[PDB]
Amino acid sequence: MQIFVKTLTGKTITLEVEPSDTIENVKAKIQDKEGIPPDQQRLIFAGKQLEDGRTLSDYNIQKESTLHLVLRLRGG
């Protein structure tokens, strides 16, 4: 599967994750292809904070995922 992520610039970044991943590795997956650390990469899904040790089959998304990334105050 892939999902969107709104962040940075480049008409939304596309993000190859399956409906079985763990948010620990997804936060990784994104932060790694975004060339950024977890100390700024901030995983949300649908207005929910995530638990890292949680499976994608519970958080349950396809396309509508668009988990988006927010930073401010932290980082500098």
Image (cartoon, grey):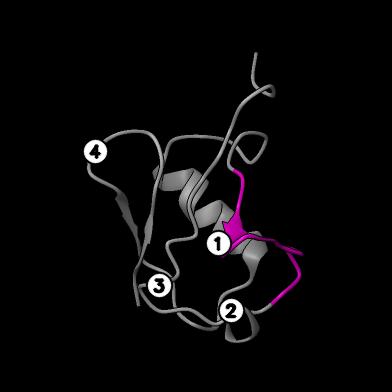
- Inter-mark Cα distance, 1 to 2: 9 Å
Q: Which is more foreground, mark 3 or mark 1?
A: 3
- Inter-mark Cα distance, 4 to 3: 19 Å
Mark with earlier residue (2, 3): 2
Looking at the picture, which amino acid does disc 1 mark? Val
* SS for callout 2: helix
Residue corresponding to mark 1: 26
Mark with earlier residue (1, 2): 1
**Span highlighted in magenta in the image:** 42-54
Looking at the picture, which amino acid does disc 4 mark? Gly
Residue 61 sits above or below residue 9 on the image: below
Which quadrant, please, contains the C terminus?
A: top right
Mark with earlier residue (2, 4): 4
**In x, y percent, where is residue 41?**
58, 41
Say the numbered circle drawn on residue 54: none
Q: Are marks 4 and 3 in contact (CB under 8 Å)?
A: no
Badge 3: residue crowd in 10 Å (few <14, some 14–19, many ≥20) = few
Q: Which is more foreground, mark 4 or mark 3?
A: 3
Residue corresponding to mark 4: 10
Residue corresponding to mark 2: 56
- Inter-mark Cα distance, 3 to 1: 16 Å
Query: Residue at point 38% right, 34% down?
Result: 8
Task: Tell me the chief SS of the magenta region.
Answer: loop
Residue corresponding to mark 3: 64
Q: Nearer the viewer, residue 60 or 46?
A: 46
Query: Residue at point 40% right, 79% down?
Result: 62
Q: Residue most toward the bottom?
A: 57
